Amino acid sequence: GSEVEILKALLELKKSTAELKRATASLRAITEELKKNPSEDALVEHNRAIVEHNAIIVENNRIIAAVLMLIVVAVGMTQEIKKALEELVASTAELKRATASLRAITEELKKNPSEDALVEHN
Amino acid sequence: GSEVEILKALLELKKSTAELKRATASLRAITEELKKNPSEDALVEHNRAIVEHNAIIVENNRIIAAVLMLIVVAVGMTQEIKKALEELVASTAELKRATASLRAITEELKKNPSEDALVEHN
Image (cartoon, chains in turn red, blue):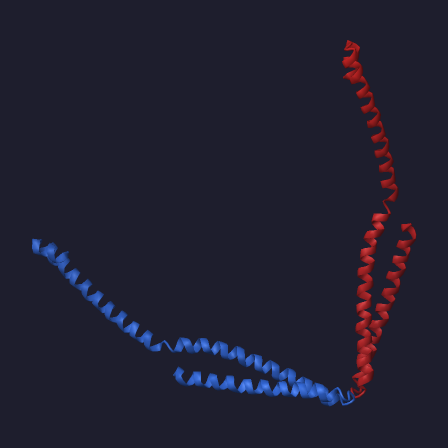
C-alpha cells in the first residue's frame, strides 16, 4: 500500500525539483540574453510567461505532495488499526458473554435465592 | 493667509482632476489601439509607464492636499486664538493685581490687625 505511494511521492519531489532548477536556469538565461536587445519582445514575454507557469506548477506539486503525505500517514496505520479492532471485537464478545451469564444468574437468584447464587452474582 | 492658500488647494484639485481624466483617456486609447498590433512594443510599454506615473502623481496630489487642508484649518483660527490670548493676558494681569493687593492687605492686617483689615482680606 503506502510503501509504493510514498516512493512515488519521493519520485515526484525529485522531478519537481529538477523542473525548478531548469525553470530557474531559463529564467536567468532569459534575463541575460533578452536584455541585450529588448526589441525581441515576443521571445522575452513568452519565456517570462513560461517561467511563471513553471514556478506555479512547482509550488502546486509541493502542496499536493504535502497533502498526500497526510493521506499516506493515515494509510500506514492500517495494521495497527486492524489489530486494535480485533481486540475490540474480542472484548465486545466477552462482554456479551458476561452479560448473558449475569442475566441467567439474575433469573436463577430470583427464582431460587440461594446464598451461592448471591456469591455468583458478585 | 488661508484665504489664498485654500483657493490654491482648490485649483490644485481642479488640475489633478483634469490630469486624471486625460490620463484615463490615454489609458483606454492605448489599450484599445495597441491590442490591434502588439508588435509596437516600445509604444505600448512607454505609454503604460506614462499612465502608471500619472496615476501615482494624482494619488499623491490628493494626499498632499488632504494634509495641507489640516494646516489650513489650523491657520484659519488665528484670530480666534489671538482673541483668546488677549483675554488670557488681561486675566493674568488682573490676577497679578489681585495678588499684589492681597499681599499689601496681609501686611496691613498683621501690622495693625483692625477688623476692617480682616474684612478687606475676605
